Image (cartoon, coloured by chain):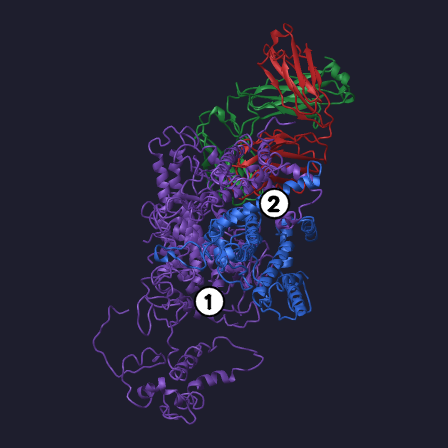
């Protein structure tokens, strides 16, 4: 049912036979991997639900003489290894769960009278990158899609449209809307990116025995989070193993590689950039070229918004408190 | 790709040569075309009718003349000595009669010479095929020349015709010539036990215990009855990390440039033999016809290897001790095991010919058994030859080991067995040996740094003549050992590249094995605890038994941790070989200095960040002995720079910063707040005129970003307090109360920047007053906190259309103050509440 | 560089007790910790060990299941929870650090704490009882007699005993405590003096049982 | 995993070479550390990795290893090296310490000044027996004490206490406390302590009568 509702979230929002389908399939892969980690006890979230679920799963798969390592091993090989016997083929618990995911997607597609996507047709699902890395890729993909969305909005709306900005799509009051969306969406993303990069820098190339938490990150060798995401977001999203793409992000509208160091002095340190994804720092600090074209009027209209919205807040505190002053 | 590495690809296989005689070129001489990755065969552009002039002809030749050459298995089945009572049934009535008939029958082999070779060579039926009505059709366009050159016209050209096809291998004994001159020198079923050998790939925790499965086959052994010893009479020095052994030493194609081949391994005796029949100079002919005969040769070669190791380590690499020679002997023993099992990961001139001859030996002798290509039983013949060789080595290894010890000396009083190191993959053995070398050299290079460069008699003291004479020169010796490329100070080990580069290659390979070995299909028994787990086979006979192949070993080696060479190496290394500085392989020191001097990442000392402050992050392969970052290169760290390793208060902001930095400035135009890791563009081309200045907008953005981030940060380190509550002789003298006293300094800078920004609105709001444009700190911070609420508790800030929460207001005014133009305190109080620890004061209890 | 333990206490048999160990200038985040106990007048014995990230906790075979070890790095402490304590676990418990940061629980213990007594018994902190030991003309051996007092049944935490307010130092052989069958400690504090000096000066032995705040100052003939 | 350390009471004199052995049952190849503990203090780690002398330790110590035999060697025994040495191994699981070897100063043989301190009248009022035999300034440490209640053997009713080797003279003092009830106290007449010491030609009897 999670797969069903997740497909219902992604696919009908935009009818791109691939883009919507591929995004939904990547989201379902992520949700399935998170379910796997909840079962295996590797999940990073102990919320109101998963905390008690984790404790009682430890009870179910535990015993008197079973330590934490033994219990985690028991959960892991109950999930991964075929700990179910059926009159059908040798289905492991992982396979049954993935088949349930597929069934939910089929229900949703039947309801929409669409065609079952070729992705989600894969019978076997590859290894799960460590939960933090999967979430990092999700963060990057979401950031980049929303970045293209918001920046194209501000491009065609606030900073001069193809129609003489003074006579553009803005009366200088709805351009404020686009710049407000961009600046307001950008600000928290900068703190989130700082936190995730600081965690990556202490987590990469760590085994189980070295990582602060018990899970291993040996598979991720890359000096910086930007280099890792450069290797990862390099391609075009398909549904398997590449759940993120980054086009024209940061400053310029080309792909890898616009200026290679192969012709001057090896090598080119990206690798590969998908926009010199170092620009992630520049774009989050509003120093990229793309925003620098828009920097002036975005800031000035932001100040106008601050001024008027503050003339409103000052009279609303006194409004509903009504004890100090007017309104 | 189906073929395994030992499968000896293209078997066109004369001794480093063939029918188109060549020298050492590549692994067409003589294996592994799949890894060769080009197409090395042209039997396919051999036209399909010439490949029927092969398929009729040369396929006949090989497989069916082999039916009378090697599937004429031998005439050794006379069975004369022993009398037989009962047989149960008779099936071989036609076997031997049609076997001798099988070269005398006019109806199966004279009806395979002058009837079927009437289609092969004596073509009476389809005579030198002329024209086909019930015969072959050719597509002459590319095969027409063959008609003239072989069938029914002129047939004279170079070896371009004959010699490369297998022509005379079938008892061609023309003797029409006599030679009187003498060009001669002086004249001249099976048993199958299975075990649980306890490998100790460790000495430390090792969550689970290792146990590999090996197959003893006592019928493949000498007979019994140990020690016996007397016979005799039977210099590289550069880890060759190179590769693809073009034809010289090096590593297989799949480990190329990846782990480095020890000089000991490339110098071991067996690997320096293109034969086992060459084991003795005196004897110059085949010697191995029985299992014991084959074994005695291995005994000889192992004994001579022991002799060599004695001649080399005691006392030329040994100091009169035994541990060094013992370790070298263990490693050589394991390398012998891999070299005869065929699973070695390296090559030279003699390997890939030794392996061929070894396959022929383990072939004939012992061959019979192997046959259960499809099998059905497990005591049973060894399925494939490779497993038979593995079983031969798993037995019979006792004798080789004792031979090795005899070859050294030990044998009673200096030996006091069978080390299980031969059950560890050659990759990991090479890694361990290379690291032990590096640690030996590092220990040498670190002894003197410790003696000299501890500040005066400890790493921390008065800097008074830190370099008592030049202890910085000792630190520089250590730097040139770590960073240089083997010529400017670098030691033995790496071959022309820095230790950092070689370690990176090792890590890449190790993780390649980890991912492959459990994203696999077939592997050995697990105890599930790790990452890349999806493969079909995780097998065993008894409880907890790994399948003894590389993937199974990397399955048990993972799954107890040890997913990285750092952790594996910390688990297996002895104790303290890394040097007097207690530098663990698991900690990661990120060092950063003048670009590695000899082989360069795109510069030496001026192109980039890595050029002068080189960012690389290995384990303590670092360019300082793990604690002397400051003991070397004098005076001890300041309290401020002990934050950079305490690292609870990191480095992002500078001029206005929770993050320990600044860039200035001190004037009107224009003190600014800088973010570390990104550069502000001082270009005023971003802007226009008579509005907010060119530098004013970039300031305002940097300042509002600073505001938001540092408020979040001070709340993280104050309410959470990074732990509650609250928060040296504590952590709150250094690294705390150290940035709190920074925030005040640089909120003052930011307060100076913003009162002076309202004074740049004595440069800009004197143009634009009174909108006041831009509003003062009080009002702007008020707006900032109110936005902070409206954004993420009010479903997006743009919901500011309706502002009333109608009872949140009391909390909101308590947090945010009343009557804006009063919002200086919304931050100052957070600094006057950047207190209650510094304050500190007392404290209460 | 500075480890102190808390929780040393007298507990009923079969009870529970939680020891704690702090840390000083020591970076108590990537060093393994260990707990080592020493019974009175016996040899040290490893008890527990915990990794740097607390993912690896090892216990001595005897104290297993009954002992739990844990870290708290932000508080910079390491705790040992003890349950089902027997009369044999009475020991001085030290907390120690590896001298090498590593990924293992057990290692060479470089820095040790002062330790805490964890005396386990069913006693009642009863005060001492002083008994004199009269000499004799027989004890005048080689011109030298001996005078002493024995402290009996003074559990817990053995006592300081002096002679003549610490005036006498030579010959004072105060024997170590001993746990007799009743569960109460006892000792003697004899001292050898010239037999000629017998009856000439006065001898008083002074006992100070801090746990019971008992001060007994007995003159001996 | 055990760690058999021997000898347990090695004696020596200043200037001698002292060797301590710490045989390990299993293979620990060199994960062994040596600890020195003086009376009434925390242990001090001298050697780790079985040979690597810890910084600040006097260089007269050394540690070497042969297979699973680890030996700590003090080349020149000094009066500040009189302590117990422990040889704790720390390879993997139980990290167990050794039994503990206690060095002592070796001096000339002496003889205990035996005493037969009898119970006191107010101790009788208390109701138990506090018969105490005292052995003073004797050496070597080995000495046996026996109790004869009217020349009858006693066992399980006496207790033993020993002082540590006294610093000024390297002599030992021993105290034997014999405890009896009132009933079996006045049930007998003569109480004797028998001292069996290597420095005594014959066992020495010290007795008294309750009426004496």
Q: Residue furthest top?
A: C200
Image x and y of residue D82, in percent: 51, 26
- Chain represented in red: C
Quarter of the image containing the C terminus of chain B? Answer: top right
Residue extending farthest to the right is D183
Q: Does any portion of residue C56 appear in the rendered image?
A: no
Chain ID at mark 2? A
Residue B160 visible in this rendered orientation of the protein: yes
Chain A takes which shade in the image? blue
Residue placed most toward the observer, B5 or A119: A119
Pinpoint the chain carrying mark 1: B
As rendered, which of B111 and B346 lies closer to the eye? B346
Q: Colour of chain D?
A: green
The residue that label 2 is drawn on is: A309
Q: Which mark is residue B4?
A: 1
Callout in the foreground (1, 2): 2
Q: Secondary structure at mark 2?
A: helix
Report how far apart the C-alphas of labels 1 and 2 lie in the structure.
73 Å
Q: Residue furthest left?
A: B181
Query: Mark 2, residues whose alpha carbon is within 10 Å: few (<14), some, or many (≥20)?
Result: some
Determine the secondary structure under disc 1.
loop
What x and y, as percent, mark residue C135? 66, 12
> Any idea which chain is the purple one in this picture?
B
The one of A102 and D29 positioned closer to us in this rendering: A102
**Residue closer to the observer: A197 or A253:** A253
Q: Is the residue under label 2 in contact with that under label 1 (CB below 8 Å)?
A: no
């Amino acid at each position: 049912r999670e797969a069903y509702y997740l497909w219902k979230q992604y696919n009908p929002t935009g009818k791109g036979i691939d883009d919507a389908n591929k995004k939904a399939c990547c989201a379902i892969r992520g949700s399935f991997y998170d379910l796997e980690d909840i079962i295996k006890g590797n999940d990073l979230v102990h919320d109101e639900y998963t905390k008690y679920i984790d404790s009682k799963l430890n009870e179910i798969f535990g015993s008197s003489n079973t330590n934490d390592i033994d219990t985690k091993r028991a959960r892991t090989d109950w999930w991964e290894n075929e700990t179910i016997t059926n009159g059908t083929d040798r289905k492991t618990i992982r396979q049954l769960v993935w088949d349930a995911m597929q069934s939910g997607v089929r229900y949703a597609v039947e309801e929409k009278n669409e065609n079952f996507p070729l992705c989600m047709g894969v019978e076997h699902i590859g290894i799960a990158k460590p939960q933090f890395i999967r979430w990092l890729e999700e963060w990057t993909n979401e950031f980049c899609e929303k970045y293209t969305k918001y920046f194209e909005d501000m491009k065609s709306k606030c900073d001069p449209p193809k129609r003489a900005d003074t006579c553009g799509d803005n009366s200088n009051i709805e351009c404020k809307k686009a710049c407000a969306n961009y600046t307001n969406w950008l600000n928290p993303k900068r703190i989130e990116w700082n936190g995730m990069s600081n965690y990556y820098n202490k987590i990469y190339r760590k085994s189980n025995k070295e990582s602060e938490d018990g899970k291993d990150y040996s598979m991720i060798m890359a000096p910086t989070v930007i280099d890792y995401l450069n290797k990862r977001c390099h391609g075009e999203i398909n549904g398997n193993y590449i759940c993120c793409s980054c086009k024209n992000i940061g400053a310029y509208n080309t792909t890898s590689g616009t200026v290679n160091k192969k012709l001057q002095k090896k090598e080119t340190e990206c690798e590969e950039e998908k926009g010199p994804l170092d620009l992630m720092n520049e774009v989050l600090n509003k120093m990229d070229k793309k925003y620098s074209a828009h920097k002036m009027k975005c800031t000035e209209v932001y100040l106008e918004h601050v001024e008027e919205q503050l003339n409103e807040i000052d009279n609303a505190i006194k409004d509903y408190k009504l004890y100090p002053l007017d309104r | 790709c189906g073929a395994r590495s030992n499968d000896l690809l293209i078997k066109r296989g004369w001794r480093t040569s063939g029918k188109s005689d060549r020298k050492k070129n590549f692994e067409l001489c003589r294996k592994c075309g799949h890894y060769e990755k080009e197409v090395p065969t042209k039997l396919d552009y051999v036209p399909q009718f010439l490949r029927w002039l092969t398929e009729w002809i040369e396929d006949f030749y090989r497989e069916k003349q082999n039916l009378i050459d090697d599937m004429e298995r031998h005439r050794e089945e006379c069975t004369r000595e022993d009398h037989k009572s009962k047989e149960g049934t008779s099936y071989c009535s036609t076997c031997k009669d049609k076997c001798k008939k099988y070269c005398e029958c006019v109806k199966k082999w004279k009806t395979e010479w002058e009837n079927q070779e009437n289609k092969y060579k004596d073509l009476y039926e389809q005579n030198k095929n002329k024209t086909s009505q019930k015969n072959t059709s050719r597509y002459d366009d590319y095969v027409k020349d063959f008609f003239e050159k072989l069938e029914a016209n002129y047939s004279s050209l170079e070896n371009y015709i004959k010699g490369d096809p297998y022509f005379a291998e079938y008892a061609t004994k023309l003797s029409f010539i006599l030679n009187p001159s003498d060009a001669n020198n002086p004249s001249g079923q099976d048993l199958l036990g299975i075990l649980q050998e306890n490998c100790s790939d460790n000495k430390r925790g090792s969550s689970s215990n290792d146990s590999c499965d090996n197959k003893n086959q006592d019928e493949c052994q000498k007979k019994l009855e140990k020690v016996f010893a007397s016979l005799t009479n039977g210099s590289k020095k550069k880890w060759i990390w190179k590769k693809s052994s073009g034809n010289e030493e090096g590593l297989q194609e799949e480990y190329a440039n990846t782990i480095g081949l020890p000089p000991r391994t490339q110098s071991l005796y067996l690997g320096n033999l293109p034969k086992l029949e060459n084991v003795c100079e005196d004897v110059k002919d085949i010697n191995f016809d029985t299992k014991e005969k084959f074994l005695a040769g291995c005994l000889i070669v192992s004994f001579h290897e022991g002799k060599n190791l004695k001649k080399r380590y005691p006392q030329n690499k040994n100091s009169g001790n035994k541990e060094n020679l013992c370790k070298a002997l263990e490693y050589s023993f394991a390398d012998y095991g891999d070299l005869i099992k065929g699973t070695s990961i390296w090559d030279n001139e003699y390997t890939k010919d030794l392996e061929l001859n070894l396959q022929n030996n383990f072939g004939k002798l012992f061959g019979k058994y192997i046959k259960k290509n499809n099998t059905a039983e497990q005591d049973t013949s060894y399925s494939s030859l490779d497993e038979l060789r593995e079983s031969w080595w798993n037995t019979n290894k006792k004798y080789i080991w004792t031979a090795m010890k005899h070859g050294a000396e030990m044998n009673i009083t200096t030996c006091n067995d069978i080390p299980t190191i031969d059950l560890i993959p050659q990759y990991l053995r090479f890694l361990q040996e290379w690291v032990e070398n590096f640690c030996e050299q590092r220990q040498a290079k670190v002894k003197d740094v410790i003696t000299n460069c501890k500040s005066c008699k400890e790493s921390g003291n008065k800097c008074k003549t830190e370099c008592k004479t030049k202890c910085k020169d000792e630190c520089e010796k250590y730097k040139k050992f770590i960073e240089a490329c083997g010529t400017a100070g670098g030691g033995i080990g790496t071959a022309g590249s820095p230790w950092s580069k070689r370690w990176d290659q090792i890590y890449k390979r190790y993780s390649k094995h980890i991912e492959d070995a459990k994203r696999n299909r077939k592997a050995g028994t697990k105890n599930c605890g790790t990452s890349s787990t999806t493969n079909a086979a995780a097998s065993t006979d008894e409880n907890k038994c790994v399948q003894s192949d590389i993937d199974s070993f990397f399955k048990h080696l993972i799954d107890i941790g040890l997913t990285t060479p750092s952790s594996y190496l910390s688990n297996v290394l002895d104790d303290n070989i890394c040097g007097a500085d207690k530098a663990p392989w698991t900690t990661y020191t990120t060092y950063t200095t003048t670009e590695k001097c000899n082989k360069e990442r795109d510069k030496s000392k001026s192109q980039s960040s890595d050029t002068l402050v080189v960012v690389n992050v290995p384990s303590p392969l670092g360019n300082t002995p793990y604690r002397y970052k400051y003991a070397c290169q004098c005076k001890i760290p300041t309290n401020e720079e002990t934050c950079d390793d305490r690292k609870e208060y990191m480095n992002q902001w500078s001029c206005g910063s929770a993050r320990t930095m600044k860039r200035g400035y001190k004037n009107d135009n224009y003190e600014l707040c800088k973010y570390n890791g990104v550069d502000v563009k001082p270009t005023t081309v971003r802007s226009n005129s008579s509005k907010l200045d060119g530098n004013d907008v970039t300031f305002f953005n940097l300042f509002e970003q600073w505001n938001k981030e540092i408020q979040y940060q001070i709340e993280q380190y104050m309410t959470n307090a990074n732990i509650s509550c609250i928060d040296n002789c504590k952590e709150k003298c250094k690294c705390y109360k150290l940035w709190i006293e920074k925030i005040n300094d640089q909120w003052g800078k930011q307060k100076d920047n913003y009162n002076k920004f309202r004074s740049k609105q004595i440069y800009d709001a004197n143009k634009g007053s009174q909108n006041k444009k831009v509003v003062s700190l009080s009002n702007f911070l008020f707006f900032s906190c109110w936005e902070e609420y409206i954004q993420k508790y009010f479903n997006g800030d743009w919901s500011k259309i309706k502002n009333i929460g109608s009872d949140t207001f009391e909390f909101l005014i308590k947090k945010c103050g009343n009557n804006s133009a009063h919002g200086e305190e919304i931050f100052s109080e957070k600094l006057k509440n950047a207190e209650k620890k510094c304050k500190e004061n007392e404290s209460t209890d | 560089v500075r480890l102190v333990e808390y929780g040393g206490r007298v507990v009923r048999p079969g009870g529970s007790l939680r020891l704690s160990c702090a840390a000083g200038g020591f970076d108590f985040d990537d060093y393994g910790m260990s707990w080592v106990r020493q019974a009175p007048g016996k040899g040290l014995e490893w008890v527990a060990g915990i990794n740097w990230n607390a993912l690896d906790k090892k216990y001595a075979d005897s104290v297993k299941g009954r002992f739990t070890i844990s870290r708290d790095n932000p508080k910079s402490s390491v705790y040992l929870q003890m349950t089902s304590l027997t009369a044999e676990d009475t020991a001085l418990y030290y907390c120690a650090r590896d001298l090498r940061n590593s990924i293992f629980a057990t290692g060479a213990l470089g820095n040790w704490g002062q330790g805490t007594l964890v005396i386990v018994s069913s006693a009642s902190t009863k005060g001492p009882s002083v008994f004199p030991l009269a000499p004799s003309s027989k004890s005048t051996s080689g011109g030298t007699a001996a005078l002493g007092c024995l402290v009996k049944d003074y559990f817990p935490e053995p006592v300081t005993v002096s002679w003549n307010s610490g005036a006498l130092t030579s010959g004072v052989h105060t024997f170590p405590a001993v746990l007799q069958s009743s569960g109460l400690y006892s000792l003697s504090s004899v001292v050898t003096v010239p037999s000629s000096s017998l009856g000439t000066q006065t001898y008083i032995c002074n006992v100070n049982h801090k746990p019971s705040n008992t001060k007994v100052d007995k003159k001996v003939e | 995993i055990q760690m058999t350390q021997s000898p347990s009471s090695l004696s020596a004199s200043i200037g001698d070479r002292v060797t301590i052995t710490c045989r390990a049952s299993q293979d620990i190849a060199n994960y062994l550390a040596w600890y020195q503990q003086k009376p009434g203090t925390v242990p001090k780690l001298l050697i780790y990795a079985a040979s690597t002398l810890l910084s600040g330790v006097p260089s007269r110590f050394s540690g070497r290893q042969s297979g699973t035999h680890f030996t700590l060697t003090i080349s020149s025994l000094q009066p500040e090296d009189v302590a117990t040495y422990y040889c704790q191994k720390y390879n993997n699981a139980p990290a167990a310490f050794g039994q503990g070897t206690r060095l002592e100063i070796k001096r000339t043989v002496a003889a205990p000044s035996v005493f037969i301190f009898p119970p006191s009248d107010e101790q009788l009022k208390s109701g138990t027996a506090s018969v105490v035999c005292l052995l003073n300034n004797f050496y070597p440490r080995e000495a046996k004490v026996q109790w004869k209640v009217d020349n009858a053997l006693q066992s399980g009713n006496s207790q033993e206490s020993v002082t540590e080797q006294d610093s000024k003279d390297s002599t030992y003092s021993l105290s034997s406390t014999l405890t009896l009830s009132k009933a079996d106290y006045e049930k007998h007449k003569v109480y004797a302590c028998e001292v069996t010491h290597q420095g005594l030609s014959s066992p020495v009897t010290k007795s008294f009568n309750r009426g004496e």
